[PDB]
Image: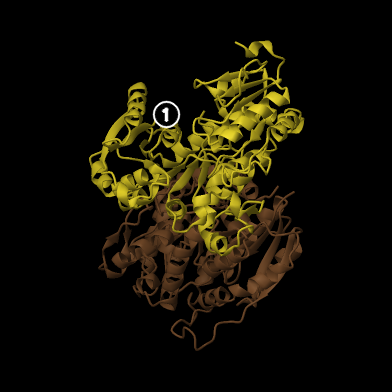
Chain colours: A yellow, B brown
Amino acid sequence: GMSPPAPADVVSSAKPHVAVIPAAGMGHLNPTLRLAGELASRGCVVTFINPSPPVSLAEATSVAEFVASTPGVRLLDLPVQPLDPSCFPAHEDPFLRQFEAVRRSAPLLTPLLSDVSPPLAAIVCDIAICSTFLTVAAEISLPAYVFFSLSAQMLSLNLAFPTVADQVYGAGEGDEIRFPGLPESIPRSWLPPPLLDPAHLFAVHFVENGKAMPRAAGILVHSWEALEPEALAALRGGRVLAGLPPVLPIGPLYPWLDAQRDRSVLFVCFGNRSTHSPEQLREMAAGLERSGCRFVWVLGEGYLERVKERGVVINGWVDQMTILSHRAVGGFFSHSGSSSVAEAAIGGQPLLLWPMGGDQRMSALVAERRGMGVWPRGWGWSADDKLIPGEEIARRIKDFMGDNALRAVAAKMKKETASAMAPGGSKDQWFDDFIARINRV
Amino acid sequence: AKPHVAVIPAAGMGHLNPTLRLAGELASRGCVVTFINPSPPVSLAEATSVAEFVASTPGVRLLDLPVQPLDPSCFPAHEDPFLRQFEAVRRSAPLLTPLLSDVSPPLAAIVCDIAICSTFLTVAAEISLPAYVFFSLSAQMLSLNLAFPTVADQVYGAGEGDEIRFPGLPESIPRSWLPPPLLDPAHLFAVHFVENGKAMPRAAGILVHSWEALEPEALAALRGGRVLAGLPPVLPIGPLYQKEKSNAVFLPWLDAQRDRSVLFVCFGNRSTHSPEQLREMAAGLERSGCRFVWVLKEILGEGYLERVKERGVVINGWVDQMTILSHRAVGGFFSHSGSSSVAEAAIGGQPLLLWPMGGDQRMSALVAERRGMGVWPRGWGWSADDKLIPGEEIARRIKDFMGDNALRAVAAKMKKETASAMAPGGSKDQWFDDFIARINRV
C-alpha cells in the first residue's frame, strides 16, 4: 500500500500533541521509544506514559534517557498494581501478566489527561495493552492509534485469526488454514503453539488484541512497502479484515572481516534468547566447520581446540548492523523473527532461517515471500527434538552461500530500504501523513 | 493490468447518476467495470439512463440483478416508491453471489451505493470480495450518518429547539435541521439511516462525493478518527459531473444574455412546493426585475408570460443542470439546496440562494453557508410546515442575492479550486489512482 494523497493546510498550525503508552519488555519498549522519537523529531510534542512504579528499573531508565535527550517530550505517571502471580501459569510468558496489570489501569488515565495542555491530538498505544485504553480514549473523544511493532504479516494474522478461529479449532492437526488477504495457505503447525489451545493465555490475549485493533482510529505498523508489499496492500484494501481502519507502514525504525573477499563470510547469530539443544548446538558447530565457508558466530559445546579455525566466534553482544552492512559478509544465519528480517533487509543480506518458536515460523514467511530467505522445512523449533545433523547443515550452508537468487533480492532490498529511509523517502511520507491527519487547524 | 470493479446503484435519479459518473470514471482509467442493475428500476428515466450509459461506454458490462419489488402489505405507512425500492434491493442482496460466480475476470472489488449498501456488504464478505460503500452525498451527511447511532437516544429525547453535538462535525446541529423522518424511530428512512450508519464501519472503505476544497474540515475529521472509531478508509472521489459536448444550443435566449446576469432557479424532481407557493414564487421573480431561467387556474397566472417575456424564461421539463450552471450568462442559482445541487454550483462557480425543503437539504445548506457561497434565509421552511412566503419577500431576497458581489467572488474562488482538483494530476486524479492501486492485484 503506497502513500495516500497528501492533503494539508500548510498555511498555519502548531505540531500536534501525541500521548504514547508502551507495553512491557525491552522488545516492545525500544520500537516505541523510536516511534516517539520519530514524532518528536518532526516537531510533535509527545507525552510518554509510564506505568508507576516500573516493573523493571532498566526500562524506566531507557525511558528517562529518551525524555532527557529529546526536547519535545513530557513524562506522565500511570499507577499500576502488579497482578497476583499465583493466578498466572508459570509455563506461559511472564510478560503476559504485566500487560494485564497495565490494561487494568486504563480508567486511571482519563482524569490524568484532563489537565493536559496543549490538548492531546492523539494517543498511540502498543497492541499488547491497547484494548482497555481504546475504550477510555473513545469516552474523551481522543483518537487512539495502535502501535503494532511486529511485521505486517503478523498483523494480518492477528486481525484475521478471530474470523477463522472456528475453522482453526475445528481443523484436524496437519490441516492448512486459509487466512484472508494472505496468498499462501499455511499449516496450523506454523502458528505459535500456544495459539492452538483456546484456553491458553496467549490465545486469549491474541484474540482479544485481534478484536480490539479494528476499534482504533488506525494502526501504525513496523513495516515498509519494499519489505511487505502484499501484506500491506491487503491491509489497506480490505482483504485481511472488513471494516479495518487505516493501516500506516511506519518503518523501518532502525578488524578480522576487512581481510576477506567480499560477500565471502557467513554471519551467524542465533540471538540472546535462542533455544538450542546441546546436541543441536554441537551439530551447528560440526556443520559450520564442515561447510568450509568463512564465518563469524555470536554465541565447551564447540569441541576441543575447535577454534583452530579460519572462522571467528564472539561471546560479547555486538551491533549486528555494522557487520551485516560490511562488504565481507554475504550471508546471515539466524533465528526467524520480525527483527532479524528487518536488519537483513537494511543490510542487504540473504537469510538462512532456523525458527526458534512462536511467531518465528511466520517471520520466515516474510523473508521467503520476498525471495531473500530460506527456511528448510525440517529445521523445526525445539519440539520433539528431531536432531538436525551437521552434514545436513554443512550442505545447506554451502547451498545457501551459493544461492544468488536470494542474494540478489536482498541486495535490491537494501537499495529499496535505503531509499525508504532517505529524506523525502517512503518512511517520511507515512509519518508526514500521520501527523497531518491528526493535526487540527 | 487494471482491476475489474462491479458497481451497484440505488433507486431514483439522484442515486443513479453519481454511480453512472463513478462507473464512467473507472472505465476512463482503464478499469473494466460491471454495472449491476436491480431489475426492474422504478422509473423509465433510470432504465433509459442505464442502457444509454452501458451502450455509450466501452469498458462497462451489464449484469442484471432481478429484484422482486416490496409487497404492498409491507411498510404500508410509507408510500414513497424510491424508499420502497431501497428496501427491495436490500432484501435481494442474497441473490448476488450466484450472479457473481460466473464473472471473469475475477472481480477486484464491488462498490455499493449507501442507500442499499448494508446487506450487500454482508454478501460480499462471505464470498471474500472487498466491498466499498459509495456515499453519493456530502462528507457532512456521511459524518452525520456515522455519528447518529452513537447519539440517537439524545436525539430522540431532545426537545424542539435543542442543538445536538455530533462528534466529527464542526458545529452543533439543531434538531429541527435533521431530516424529519429521522426524528421518527419507526420511520423506514430512520431504520435505513441507522442500519447504514452501522454498516459503513464494516466496509472495506467508503468512497464519498466530496473534495478537499468543498469540505476540508469534514474530510479531515473522517480521515483522522474524529467522527467514528474503527472507521475504514474514507476517500473523497469528487467532483463527479456529466454535462454534454458536441451538442446543439439548448436555449438561445440564455446564450444572448450578458455575463452573470441570469438567475437560474430550479427546485428539483421531488419539489414539494404548494401551488399557492408556486404563484408567489412567480410573482417574486417578476417583482425582482432580474433576468431568470426557471425550470419546473394556472400556477403562474394570466398574462404572466407576456409581462415577463424580456427577462424571464419558464421551462416545464428536463434540462441539463450542470450545463446551465457552467454557462457564462448565469450569475445565481436559486435552489432547493440538494447535496448534488451544492456540488454542481461549486463546480460552476455559482452562488446559491437556498430554500431547503426536506430531509438532508438543510445539512447541504450548511455546507454552502460554511464556505460562504450560499445564503439560506431562515424562515423559508420545510414544505411540510405550510408557511407561505410572499412574492414581495422573495423579490427582495433575490435582489440582495444577485447583488451580493462578495458572495459571487467566493463562488468564483470555489470554481477555481475545484478546477485545480479536476486538472490532471490534481487531487481527484490522485484519489482515483489511490483507489485503483488499493484495489489492484499483482
Say which quarter of the image contains residue B423: top right
Of the pair B325 and B391, the residue shown nearer to us: B325
Residue ranking furthest to the front: A304
Whole-percent x, y for residue B23 in the image: 66, 59
Of the pair A202 and B298, the residue shown nearer to us: A202
Residue with the mark numbered 1: A37
Q: Is residue B257 above or below residue A34?
A: below
Quarter of the rendering occupied by the N terminus of chain A: top right
Residue type pointed to by label 1: Gly
The chain under label 1 reads A
Whole-percent x, y for residue B114 in the image: 53, 64
Whole-percent x, y for residue A85 in the image: 31, 47
Q: Is residue B22 left or right of residue B71?
A: right
Q: Is residue B239 left or right of residue A17?
A: right
Q: Is residue B79 above or below residue A144?
A: below
- Label 1 environment density (alpha carbons within 10 Å; few <14, some 14–19, many ≥20): many
Of the pair A12 and A46, the residue shown nearer to us: A46
Residue A415 seen in the figure? no
Quarter of the rendering occupied by the C terminus of chain A: top left
Of the pair B19 and A414, the residue shown nearer to us: A414
